[PDB]
């Protein structure tokens, strides 16, 4: 009886490797946990992590790749602090398609005048039509979240923001597919969701965007400072950068971002087919054109969800050792998380369970 | 195997980490994959906090939070949370080395910073506290307990006329008991003495929350983080786990009191050799202020003898003793003597020093 976890996870071979190397990394006589950030040994590690980010995503040479502490929510502060002063107005445009872009917009209010570019959504079930976005020509930047982790809304295109600096929260689908980096001013992602373990955040920053940081910006969070120090302004989250490195290498060894995209396709289409042929039994609230490949929320019984049937679904799932499928407090129902490390075989099992559960309970 | 005079983990901690990596206590999941919102992790961050409270005897009116951004994070996080306490937005700073100097410089981004004493010509002492020019309208007074690069350590708590006292304890945190009730904020990067890089522990008096500036990033705002048990966003889960073990090891080895006993033995072994080398090994810090954590010294003369110093480090290395090179901005030699660095380890360093003094002194 081993557990199946529909949440973020490390590939198994990556844990084996961490574990083997833990007391005496590669023969250096020391643990990465113990390694000075000023050592040529750590320099090599951090260098290889930057390199892998650039290779895997195909990051053009006019972008800085930096590794920061603070996580996603750190960047909700760091983005405005670094960038709201791009133009003197200190205005920014925000696109709000879920809980995460909502928090980000709320946070940015501390630093400037935030314009939410579309009518506020009643339910987070779609991306408001980008061609109706009410953009500020004097916005310092336009901000949006690529993948809304709790609501299952994912951008599968790069919106036209009329030449503005585009900033993107990519935390929960980072390196789940190729990305045309050159469309962006800033991309960021906490490593934990998809690309490693908590403690580090990758920030990709166009090289012409440094140098507008507010006075109040903490130095550890200032893109200019961090990029001029190759992420060693202070002590970075060493082990996390190490762990990320090994995950990125794993992505490379698995065929790269393109392979990841193929594996998300398969995984989600498996689950979405079941929903879309359940003739009402499973109800995903997201308009199909905006459905996440990473997080699939749904209800059981009907669109408002049937509490009894959902409890039984979770209870039985727990009984089969399928963990972490409970939908978020704010949405209710079920959520299936399908990151790079969640295998096709895991997902085949969830699917088989859903089909059986349908057979038994659909009146 | 080697011997490192730098921050390390106790060997036994690393053994447990490795033992449990793939499957934390039979739960079927790594601490590295653990959801920060799970009951499994809740146990952990709860255990870690309680060990701090226990090991330093933190009073009840203090919050203990775990944050990202490092000691340097706190260089901003302190003023951002507190410079606004009094409306002038001033802080007094005591600058006794590299780190308090950075801290004082960073704090300029958020208020008017006054350095309480004249600037030292060289970091070789704590300028006497009665000579300090304290501002009664300052929001708080800031100092660095242990200067890692210059070997200058407070062995007392400064009288700041009742001001809110703020103290960077990164490099000597839990090497001794601390009267926490005397402070407004204590903070510490975990990596120097207490664990691994990626978490910073902040001890904050609960009446000092919500004076934070509007510009304070929520994840660094004491109030936000304390009101959420450091679970406002995803915490550095692994770093917290690791630190928890380290504190557990301190506890099992006799707590803050025993570390102080160790720190005394370890450092007096080196300072003994230094002071009786009749000028062969010279330590630049005044005796009354010398660090128990970091021991910087020159060989040959007070200014350092390059040939003797190279040879020292050369031979040290051949005896597998690593990381003894003094910091690039100071030259010479530095022995770091954190908790994890044993009496047996220092014992070998000392033997070497005596014999090097023997083979080379004229
Ligand atoms: C997890 C999440 C965040 C927040 O990340 P933290 O490290 O907890 O601050 C931001 N955006 C998305 C899409 C997320 O899934
Ligand atoms: C190492 C050190 C720091 C640096 O902290 P970071 O985590 O690297 O930002 C701060 N204060 C003291 C006393 C230190 O020794």
Image (spheres, coloured by chain):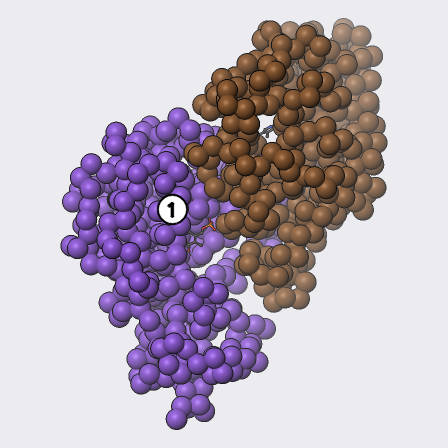
Chain colours: A brown, B purple
Residue shown at the point (43%, 34%) measured from the top left:
A216
Tell whether circle 1 marks a residue whose Cβ is less than 8 angstroms from ligand 2. no
Q: Is residue A33 left or right of residue B47?
A: right
Q: How many marks?
A: 1
Residue shown at the point (80%, 40%) measured from the top left:
A256
Image position of A283 with respect to B357: above or below: above
Residue A85 seen in the current view: yes
Residue A111 placement (x, y as % from top left) = 46, 24
Image position of A44 with respect to A243: above or below: below
Residue A289 placement (x, y as % from top left) = 77, 14
The one nearer the camera, A138 or B4, is A138
Residue lying farthest to the bottom in this orientation: B362
Q: Is residue A357 left or right of residue B177?
A: right
The one nearer the camera, B220 or B84, is B84
Q: On the image, numbered disc 1 is attached to which residue?
A: B105
- For the C terminus of chain B, the quadrant is bottom left
Image position of B340 with respect to B235: above or below: below
The answer to which quarter of the image holds residue A32 is: bottom right
The answer to which quarter of the image holds residue A148 is: top right
The one nearer the camera, A280 or A32, is A32
Residue A5 seen in the current view: no
Residue A267 placement (x, y as % from top left) = 80, 28
Residue shown at the point (42%, 31%) measured from the top left:
B216
Q: Is residue A13 left or right of residue A141?
A: right
Density class for disc 1 (Cα within 10 Å; few <14, some 14-19, many ≥20) is some
Residue B134 placement (x, y as % from top left) = 19, 46
Residue shown at the point (45%, 91%) measured from the top left:
B359
- For the N terminus of chain B, the quadrant is bottom right
Image position of A102 with respect to A14: above or below: above
Secondary structure at badge 1 equals helix
Q: Chain of mark 1?
A: B
């Amino acid at each position: 009886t081993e557990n199946l976890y529909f949440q973020s996870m490390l590939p198994h071979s990556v844990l084996l490797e961490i574990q083997k190397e833990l007391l005496d990394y590669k023969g250096v006589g020391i643990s990465v946990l113990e390694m000075s950030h000023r050592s040529s040994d750590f320099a090599k590690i951090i260098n290889n992590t930057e390199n892998l980010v650039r290779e895997l995503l195909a990051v053009p040479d006019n972008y800085k790749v930096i590794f920061l502490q603070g996580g996603g929510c750190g960047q909700f502060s760091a983005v405005p602090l670094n960038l709201i002063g791009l133009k003197a107005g200190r205005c920014a445009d925000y696109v709000v398609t879920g809980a995460w872009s909502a928090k980000a917009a709320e946070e940015a209010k501390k630093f400037g005048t935030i314009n939410i570019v579309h009518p506020k959504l009643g339910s987070y079930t779609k991306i408001p039509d980008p061609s109706t976005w009410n953009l500020n020509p004097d916005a310092s930047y336009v901000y949006y979240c690529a993948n809304e982790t709790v609501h299952g809304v994912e951008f599968d295109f790069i919106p036209d923001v009329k030449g503005a600096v585009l900033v993107c929260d990519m935390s929960s689908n980072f390196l789940s597919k190729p990305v045309d980096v050159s469309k962006f001013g800033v991309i960021f992602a906490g490593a934990q969701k998809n690309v490693g373990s908590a403690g580090v955040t990758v920030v990709i920053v166009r090289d012409d965007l440094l140098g507008f940081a507010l006075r109040e910006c903490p130095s550890v969070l200032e893109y200019k400072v961090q990029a001029g120090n190759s992420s060693l302004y202070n002590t970075p989250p060493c082990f996390s950068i190490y762990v990320m490195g090994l995950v990125l290498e794993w992505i490379k060894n698995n065929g790269g971002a393109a392979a990841m995209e193929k594996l998300s396709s398969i995984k989600s289409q498996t689950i979405y087919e079941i929903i879309d042929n359940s003739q009402g039994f499973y109800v995903c609230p997201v308009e199909p054109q905006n459905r996440s490949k990473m997080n699939i929320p749904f209800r059981i019984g009907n669109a408002k969800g049937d509490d009894a049937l959902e409890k039984r679904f979770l209870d039985k799932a727990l009984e089969l050792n399928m963990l972490s499928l409970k939908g978020h407090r704010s949405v209710g129902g079920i959520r299936a998380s399908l990151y790079n490390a969640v295998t096709i075989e895991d997902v085949q099992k969830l699917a088989a369970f859903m089909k059986k559960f349908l057979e038994m309970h659909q009146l």
